[PDB]
Amino acid sequence: GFCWQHTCLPSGCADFPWPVGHQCFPD
Image (cartoon, rainbow, N blue to C red; front, side, top):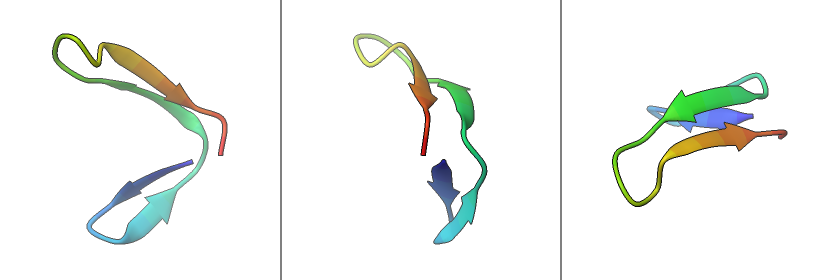
């Protein structure tokens, strides 16, 4: 999962800028 504004949403992918890149959060 991924947290946004302390609200944690389900596992998924998010596109971050370089060099973090496209991250996928299984939790």
